[PDB]
Amino acid sequence: SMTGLTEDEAKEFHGIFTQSMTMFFGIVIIAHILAWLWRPWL
Amino acid sequence: KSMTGLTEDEAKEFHGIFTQSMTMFFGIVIIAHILAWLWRPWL
Amino acid sequence: NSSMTGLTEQEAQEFHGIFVQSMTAFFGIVVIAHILAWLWRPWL
Amino acid sequence: TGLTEQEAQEFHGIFVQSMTAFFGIVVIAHILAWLWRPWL
Amino acid sequence: SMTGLTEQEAQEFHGIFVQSMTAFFGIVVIAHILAWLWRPWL
Amino acid sequence: TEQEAQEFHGIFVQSMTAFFGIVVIAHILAWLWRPWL
Amino acid sequence: LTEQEAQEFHGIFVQSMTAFFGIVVIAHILAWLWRPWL
Amino acid sequence: SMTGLTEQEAQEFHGIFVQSMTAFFGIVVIAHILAWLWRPWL
Amino acid sequence: MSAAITEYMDVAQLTIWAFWFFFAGLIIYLRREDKREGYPLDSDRTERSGGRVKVVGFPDLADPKTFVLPHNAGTVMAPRVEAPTSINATPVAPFPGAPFEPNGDPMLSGFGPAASPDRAKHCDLTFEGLPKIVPMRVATDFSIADKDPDPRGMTVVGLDGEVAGTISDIWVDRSEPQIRYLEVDVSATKKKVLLPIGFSRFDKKAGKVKVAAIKAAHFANVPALSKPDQITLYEEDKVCAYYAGGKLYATAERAGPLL
Amino acid sequence: PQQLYKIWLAFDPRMALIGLGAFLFALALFIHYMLLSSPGFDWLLGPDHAPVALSAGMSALPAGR
Amino acid sequence: AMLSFERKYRVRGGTLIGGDLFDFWVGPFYVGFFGVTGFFFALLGVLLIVWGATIGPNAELQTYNIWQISIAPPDLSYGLGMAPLTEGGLWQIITICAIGAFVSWALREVEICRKLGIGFHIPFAFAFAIGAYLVLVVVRPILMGAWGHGFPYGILSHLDWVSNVGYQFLHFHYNPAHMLAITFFFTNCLALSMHGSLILSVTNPQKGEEVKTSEHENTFFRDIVGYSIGALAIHRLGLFLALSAVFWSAVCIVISGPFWTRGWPEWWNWWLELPLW
Amino acid sequence: SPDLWKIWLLIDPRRVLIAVFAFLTILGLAIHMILLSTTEFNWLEDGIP
Amino acid sequence: MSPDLWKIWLLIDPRRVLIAVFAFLTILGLAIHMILLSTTEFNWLEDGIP
Amino acid sequence: MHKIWQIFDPRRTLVALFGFLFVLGLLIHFILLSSPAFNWLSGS
Amino acid sequence: MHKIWQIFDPRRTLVALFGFLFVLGLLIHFILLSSPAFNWLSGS
Amino acid sequence: MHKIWQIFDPRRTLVALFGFLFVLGLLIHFILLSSPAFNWLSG
Amino acid sequence: MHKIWQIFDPRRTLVALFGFLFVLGLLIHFILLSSPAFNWLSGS
Amino acid sequence: MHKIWQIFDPRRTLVALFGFLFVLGLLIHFILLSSPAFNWLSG
Ligand code: BCL
Ligand code: BCL
Ligand code: BCL
Ligand code: BCL
Ligand SMILES: CC[C@H]1c2cc3[nH]c4c(c3C)C(=O)[C@H](C(=O)OC)c4c3nc(cc4[nH]c(cc(n2)[C@@H]1C)c(C(C)=O)c4C)[C@@H](C)[C@@H]3CCC(=O)OC/C=C(\C)CCC[C@H](C)CCC[C@H](C)CCCC(C)C
Ligand SMILES: [Ca+2]
Ligand SMILES: [Ca+2]
């Protein structure tokens, strides 16, 4: 609206954003479980 | 008429080139790291 | 309109051909120089 | 600020729910931290 | 066509440029042969 | 004009050659003073 | 420049140059007599 | 021609200059003779 | 709570890194503020691309900022669009980065040092709405300081020391009392022209005004006013630019070089 | 030189005399100062300048690398 | 490249040396003859600094850490003669290149302002900083007697040089020209802060208000301190303070050693030995 | 919040992308450097293997 | 993983992101090489081997 | 209280709040690091 | 892969590439000259 | 390879090339003068 | 080879050439003075 | 050759040459004073 974006475009932008965050927060979990296997910190 | 001026059939072509041009670079990186592991492993 | 830079397809293919030929000559010279340098004294 | 009364309704409605989700995450993290090493 | 030169003028300039550069490289080759005969660096 | 672009070479090249000759004379005398190579 | 007055300046420029060089050469000869450097 | 000095004014001024400089240089050379007599620098 | 975070890091190192981050942000902000006048740039890259690629560099431009002018003079946006113009010159050589030649008669050409934009066609105003720069014939409450020459009746001489007229009136500034212009009554066309103070030297011994910008015969082409009691921002700029052009175009020896 | 009087047709004598006088005075001051600095030609020390001799193993300046 | 209103001002002529040989623009820059000379002086100076870092003080203390790279002047036993390249002649060559580059920059500015038709205040002001550098590396070493009195070229080492030179006089705060220069520097900083604050306050008023006029600028400082200096006079004063600071700093450094070889507090004894007290 | 997507109606979606990319890159660099600063997690001078 | 991701080139222009990524990759490569050259273990020039 | 947004700009408030929360979290993590009893990157 | 020249201007790309390559060559030579192992002016 | 002069203009290119060649020659000579094994001014 | 002296001004070229030669001569003389085996003033 | 004054201003050439010669002489005297074998300001 203010930023020149309609509602129907905002909905699918939100969907794609969520689907990208899912993969980004999925790969980090693998990285952190490998790091814990390597050298635990807690 | 989006905020870049690229038509619907132009962003598709740019993406199609971009994915391959990045995959080959990553493959070269993978080969270089496989060779570097056999030289002086760090973990 | 025209292309984002103003070059047509043929005018951007002639440049690509000359560019890749120059790059290939450069890389061949570099490869020969590195082979000679390794024959001089290795680093790994 | 050039906002109508009804425009200032759903914004608050979303704002409170987002804040309370953040607070729930904070509470879980703090309970786990106390289970790790208490500070009192 | 950004340099304000046509094909013919570019070719005419390039001929003299390449001839001068070749004449400049010959002297360098001779000087390096003499310097190698003076005190080899390899 | 045509009377400078193609003619003024005839004096420029002669002056350059005359300068190089004096340079060579100086270098020969310097070598006879103290060789470096 | 006009041939009537273009080397008339050169005519006295040459003489001034020669006069400047004569005393320079005399000074250098005296300096070599005082303490040779080569 | 540039500085607006008539061919007589310049020729008049040059004589005064070339006589005053003569007197100045005579004074200077006398001073240098005395100074060399005092303590030679060569 | 101590001064050593780890075996190597301490507090005074984290503080300097935080300062560097803040400084990078501040530099980006300042460079974005710098780009409110004259962008996007005019280059060959834009025109070759058929007006498609716009050259702004990094960072890009900011959202428009509004100035409101007093006495209902209007509103001006800090980043705005302006109409591309056709210059009065012709390139010396076709390669990029080459200079231009001031086609025509250089003084009356509007190019080079004798160039100016087109400002608003209204007079600058005071806090009460009066015109700001006016002659002393209407600012009667003004006066010349004591023990000072009072340059009325002084002869004005040109670049070559030839008289080109006499001073007739003095234009002052109501808000800040100082002299902004001199009025010269040219004795070659029976006209009156303005002369900025920045281009005149006061020879108070013999009572003269020296104008080293243009010669005596050039005082006949100075741009004129619309009304004899006030001036606008457009005309002031035109008058100043005409004199500024003489710093390069006055004589044949002023284009250079020394050797 | 024969016709040197033409040199005053290009340079204004009124400025030339000022410049020459100023330059000559500056040169004289510089040369006097240079002599005053030198250890051989320093007349302010007096005609009867006798520096102090060192009778024993003494040195006016400390040693330095 | 060009601003949207710049093409009107790219005119031919106004050069000092060169004429039409080097009269062109390279990107946004104007080069000219002095542009070529200055650029290549700077390039050779940079390359020699990098080579001096490559050689290092030794083969063991050589390092590419930017804080620790230092190129040092010769020994005091060489006097004013020319030192070997590895023992301090590289410093002398780099000093010559730096002087050439600075002078070329100033002359290029003179050419630019001749082209634009404006005054010559900017190169004139730059000449003061150039003169301060020249006093640092040319005048003081000649008066003292050796090139070894110059400072080393390094980011952290020239601070060590400043500290040791300062402590050669046991208390450098008591240097009077030093006090004058410091007063000018602090006053310049204060005046700059006030000029910026006032211009921004007038140009960016309270919300829902129009741009302020010239009377407000004078009224503000007449109501704070009882006097206002004006729009042109504030720039006059800023230039005056900024140049006086540098002039008095050059005076303060050129009298330390050449004209005074004792502690700086002792210099004040003339005041304490007056017969009044 | 099930109607959170309207946050894209007020903030332009072509700036959050750049901001998050730069923020994630800088955060990753900072965490890698903090780990390198320690003597327990430094993988370049740990002495293994 | 979001097949319509190609729409991302309608938001940000490709040319400036290409310039940015090329500069960033060059800087990162130089930094990593210098960091490795700054350590005793991985300095392949001063290791002495072979 | 749903009239508070008639005074404060929602966008400005959200941006400032996110920045403030991020800086506060960073500060608290660093303070915990500086305490030898809570430094988790050392031994135990 | 010849349509890249319809996005980038060849002249600016060429000047930037040549500058980067020249600087890189100088940098590598200086890095090699700073180590006694590979210094060919005194080590060879 | 003769259309390069339709991309680069001779007037600026030749100036830059000559300047860089001169600076490179000076750098190589200075590097040699600083290496005792190749200094030719030691007798 | 001579097709240069048409828009390449000889008058402007001579000044630059003389300056270049003078600077080069000064540099070479000072470099010779920096070496003890060729310094013709201090020696002998 | 003698037409060199057709392509050069005689006045400016003299003004520049005199300063050049003065600076050159000053430099040579400075160099001679800095060599203890040729310094004449002793004894
Ligand atoms: C200390 C123990 C391990 C180690 C433990 C971890 C752990 C735990 C993590 C990493 C992660 C990373 N490590 Mg590691 N890592 C080690 C040593 C290294 C060394 C080295 C010189 O030895 C290098 C070069 C790296 C490099 C990396 C990066 C690949 C990655 C962080 C980049 C980032 O945050 O992007 C963020 C910036 C962006 C802009 C991403 C945005 C994504 C967008 C949507 C996609 C566009 C492309 C984007 C620009 C790049 C995508 C790359 C992917 C995010 C991977 N690590 C040591 C050996 N490392 C992190 C990771 O795996 O991230 C997935 C992570 O969680
Ligand atoms: C223990 C040491 C002593 C002390 C010993 C000294 C010594 C020794 C010196 C000073 C000097 C100064 N001291 Mg002190 N000083 C002390 C304490 C102080 C204190 C304080 C708060 O206590 C202050 C405020 C000062 C302040 C000052 C200034 C008056 C002065 C430095 C400014 C200057 O000279 O500008 C001069 C500016 C320049 C030289 C800039 C030149 C730059 C030119 C233009 C070259 C271009 C730069 C670059 C190449 C361009 C390209 C760069 C990038 C590629 C773009 N001192 C202590 C007590 N001080 C210095 C001085 O007076 O020098 C004249 C000086 O030598
Ligand atoms: C010291 C004991 C524990 C520890 C004790 C705690 C405690 C207690 C807390 C954290 C919290 C956090 N810790 Mg921890 N943490 C430790 C060590 C680490 C290390 C490390 C290098 O070892 C890292 C990278 C982190 C990182 C984090 C973040 C995930 C989180 C801070 C969020 C924030 O700042 O919001 C600021 C960001 C915004 C406001 C963004 C703006 C709005 C956004 C869009 C909405 C979401 C906000 C934020 C992103 C929520 C993230 C939650 C996710 C589920 C990760 N911790 C050690 C091991 N940590 C906090 C937390 O859980 O927050 C949720 C918290 O309360
Ligand atoms: C171990 C150290 C070895 C050594 C081992 C190597 C190895 C291995 C290599 C070099 C290479 C180079 N070395 Mg080495 N080198 C040594 C000592 C030297 C000495 C010396 C004083 O002793 C000199 C002068 C050099 C000089 C050089 C350069 C010729 C070259 C870097 C090219 C460049 O920067 O292009 C940058 C500039 C450009 C790319 C732009 C200019 C090119 C033109 C204008 C563009 C068109 C391209 C054209 C069609 C084809 C290429 C032509 C190029 C001129 C080659 N080396 C010692 C003996 N050297 C590299 C090389 O061979 O390059 C070919 C290389 O791989
Ligand atoms: C005199 C009043 C103040 C002043 C004025 C001033 N400075 C100026 C100007 C003016 C009016 C310009 O017009 C000019 C300019 O272009 O500004 C943008 C400039 C300038 N002042 C600069 C810097 C500068 N000014 C300083 C000071 C001051 N400048 C004074 C306080 C300082 C200080 C205090 O340190 C610095 C660092 C430049 C940004 C610029 C001049 C740029 C220039 O000359 O460029 C040509 C040279 C090069 C590009 C490369 C030189 C090559 C050398 C080999 C470099 C190294 C030399 C050095 C001796 C060795 C290393 C030293 C170590 C300490 C690291
Ligand atoms: Ca390891
Ligand atoms: Ca190895």
Image: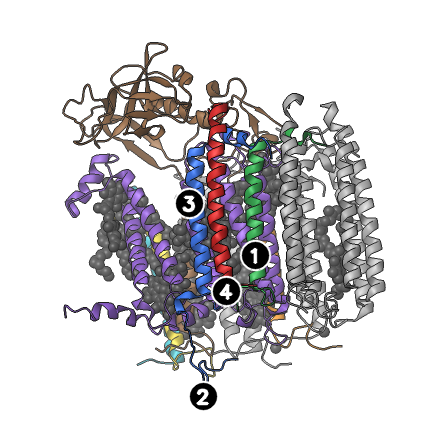
Chain colours: D cyan, H red, I brown, J blue, K purple, M orange, N yellow, R green
Q: On the image, numbered disc 3 is attached to which residue? A: J22
Image position of N29 with respect to K193: above or below? below
Q: Amino acid at mark 4?
A: Arg
Q: On the image, numbered disc 1 is attached to which residue? A: R29
Q: Are marks 1 and 4 on the same chain?
A: no
Query: Residue at the location (49% across, 30% down)?
Result: K9
Q: Nearer the viewer, residue D7 or K205?
A: K205
Residue found at the very far bottom of the displayed protein: J56
Query: Residue at the location (45% across, 88% down)?
Result: J55
Image position of K79 with respect to K220: above or below? below
Subunit bearing disc 4: H
Residue K266 picture location, percent across and down:
29, 72
Image quadrant in which the C terminus of chain K is located: bottom left
Classed neighbour count for the residue bearing mark 4: other residues with Cα under 10 Å, few (<14), some (14–19), many (≥20): few
Q: Which mark is residue H39?
A: 4
Q: Is residue H36 left or right of residue K222?
A: right
Which quadrant of the view contains residue I221? Answer: top left
Q: Name the element at disc 4.
A: loop
Beta carbon of the mark 1 residue lies under 8 A of ligand 5: no
